[PDB]
Image (cartoon, rainbow, N blue to C red):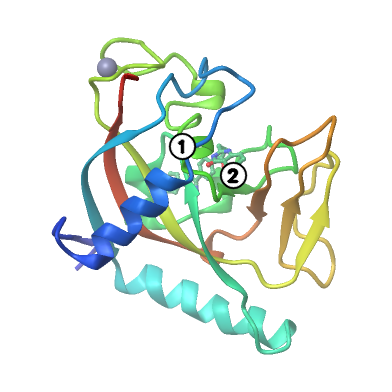
Amino acid sequence: QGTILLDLAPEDKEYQSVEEEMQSTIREHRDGGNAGGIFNRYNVIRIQKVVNKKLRERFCHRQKEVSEENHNHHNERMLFHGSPFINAIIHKGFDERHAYIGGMFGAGIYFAENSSKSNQYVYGIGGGTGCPTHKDRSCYICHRQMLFCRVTLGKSFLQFSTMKMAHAPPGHHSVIGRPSVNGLAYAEYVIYRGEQAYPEYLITYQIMKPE
Ligand SMILES: O=C(CCc1nc2ccccc2c(=O)[nH]1)Nc1ccc(-c2nnc(-c3ccccc3)o2)cc1
Ligand SMILES: [Zn+2]
């Protein structure tokens, strides 16, 4: 078999937990919404738990390698990811060959702890041309998708400034861009190996027009 998508009932704590994590990390972006659209609340249409035997094996297999190199601590973490490649990701997993080379920290796979940051990328860099059907970045109609993943960070190379890497720095397994006055408002997590992230949950949703 391949990937199985398990519907989480909205009355379930698991579903409830994901949503609150998603709804609760919304924030104002210095962009003004141009990228991800104006809203301060989402409408969750549904959340499905991605199940894939092979994807799990590679992630887990990679998980203990990082542990070997990080004092038996893989330092896992739940983070959001958004891009126009979600449907491929939940079937084939994260593949760094499709990593974003224009990234702040190099050709890696980017995650955020603020659902609103990943939302800016759902339709492409800087929001691209908005939704496929209406070509609107702030569309309140079309259904969007972002992931809430398990991310194996291992030993993270902490950095403030832009520095494009192809791979994690020696002895490290990830890069954490930290907030800087003339820099990042908020932190972003980067990995250079796809199998160090599992696309746990697939959230289908809509941003909501203000009140
Ligand atoms: O990470 C990015 C850039 C967009 C992005 N940037 C951020 C920057 C700071 C904080 C959070 C984010 C973020 O959520 N997304 N894009 C991206 C695009 C595709 C991938 C990908 N991984 N596997 C595939 C794949 C696999 C099989 C077939 C086709 C594609 O694509 C990974 C990352
Ligand atoms: Zn639309």
- Provide residue 146's location: percent of width, then percent of height: 38, 43
At 46% from the left edge and 37% from the top edge, which residue is drawn?
A: 83
Residue 145 or 66: which is nearer the viewer?
Answer: 145
Residue 61 or 129: which is nearer the viewer?
Answer: 129
- Provide residue 76's location: percent of width, then percent of height: 56, 72
In the depicted structure, whether residue 41 falls above or below residue 80: above
- Provide residue 35's location: percent of width, then percent of height: 52, 20
Question: Within 8 Å of ligand 1, the CB of disc 1?
Answer: yes
Residue 66 or 160: which is nearer the viewer?
Answer: 160
Quadrant in which residue 10 is drawn: bottom left
Q: Which mark is residue 99?
A: 2
Q: Residue tagged by mark 1? A: 83
Q: Amino acid at mark 2?
A: Ala
Q: Which quarter of the rendering shows the C terminus?
A: top left
Question: Within 8 Å of ligand 1, the CB of disc 2?
Answer: yes
In the depicted structure, whether residue 115 falls above or below residue 149: above
Circles 1 and 2: CB atoms closer than 8 Å: no
Q: Residue furthest front?
A: 211
Q: Amino acid at mark 1?
A: Ser
- Provide residue 48's location: percent of width, then percent of height: 23, 56
Describe residue 48's horizontal placement relative to residue 138 as left or right: left
At 56% from the left edge and 47% from the top edge, which residue is drawn?
A: 112
Indicate the secondary structure of the residue bearing disc 1: loop
Q: Which mark is residue 130?
A: none
Indicate the secondary structure of the residue bearing disc 2: loop
In the depicted structure, whether residue 197 falls above or below residue 58: above
At 68% from the left edge and 37% from the top edge, which residue is drawn?
A: 103
Q: Marks 1 and 2, how far apart in space?
A: 11 Å
For the residue carrying disc 2, how many other residues have a C-alpha within 10 Å: few (<14), some (14-19), or many (20+)? some
Q: Nearer the viewer, mark 1 or mark 2?
A: 1
